[PDB]
Length: 233
Length: 233
Ligand SMILES: Cc1cn([C@H]2C[C@H](O)[C@@H](CO)O2)c(=O)[nH]c1=O
Ligand SMILES: Cc1cn([C@H]2C[C@H](O)[C@@H](CO)O2)c(=O)[nH]c1=O
Image 1 (cartoon, helix red, strand yellow):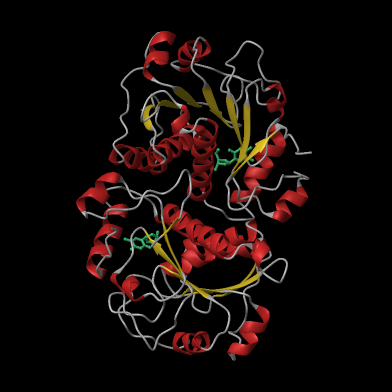
Image 2: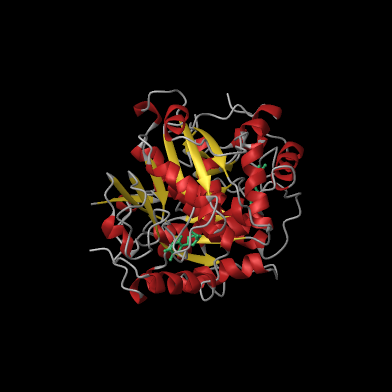
């Protein structure tokens, strides 16, 4: 079966992709985000939803996982969803400035604030994307993110988490944490994925070179045809 | 029906994407090249080919089109093809250095020379990807590309061309140039595509913003579901 990575293992793979393999951050974040959008459109196809176009709130955190979310949002728009973004803490870098301007020009709105009650999220948004924290998160959830996570915990609509459910320990999980209905593991799942109790677990990031895969014995499943996602279990 | 762009309209679309929309070169080239690999895999699926895995020669020119071929070849490898690259003139810019290193660490070999005779290409490679010149190219074919084009025009195996069949005037085509079996038009087809004679015409580069599509009256077709290509005609 597929290998579930430790936090160290994942940080080592991420290091090689940008070092030995000379991938650019731009690049792999674009493929990551596309997988994310693709898994979401496959698990929650626009046809299956009661609103048209179906609405989605994408919550983007302060780092790279956030960047994935912004990429994910605009492909989701291309796929026929009507996304909305909350992005409260934005790094002051071209990468993220660009990603913001692209979304702004796709007419995707960035909210001024997180809606404060879960009921109000539920009412406006048919799905929530958790793009807050990723694989290199180390455990100190500060405001406004704790607040956001606590609103998410009370939701009735599904949550789709990118790479790891935000607020989970990357290896141990968090039973009192958010419980996403969809998890998109990027490149390979992390050990916290073994505590995943949602219906949908997709693997994404179809860019792992065979030699990187052999070395770390990932045992990736075979992606069908030209798909950038693979549904695990 | 879909709009066929003049070279001028294509350059203005392209410039808007990198200027107002603030996409980065990397992002769009990655998506463009993935579209290419996806269209090939759809037109010439691995099961439909005599050898296993199926072999493909990718010929990359000295600018952005060649960039697309380098991305394309790496995705084709992930999709189960066995590509070989010929890349005789390589700009000294980190964009291309990177894309070359990524290909080499995918273990895709680079040829030192073009096979001199059409028959030898035919015997070694089941498909040839023409990523030599793209939409900016202005009439002038110098070495080694004239000679490579001369080899390509005598092939029996199919040629897949990225954006524009290399050696064709970007609007007027070229009665005596190469005649590809597959054309992958990126973003929107160009006027020269009305002179296309092959079996397969795909549209790729599924990143055009609606507002830009409204602006240039592209009348883009509906990509199905989460696909990054659409079969035209
Ligand atoms: C090893 C590894 C890399 N990545 C890469 C892919 C994306 O470019 C970025 C995630 O934001 O880092 C992961 O997301 N998760 C991982 O476990
Ligand atoms: C408008 C336009 C853009 N592009 C974009 C996509 C790629 O990122 C880059 C080089 O092919 O330019 C085309 O290839 N062809 C076009 O006609």
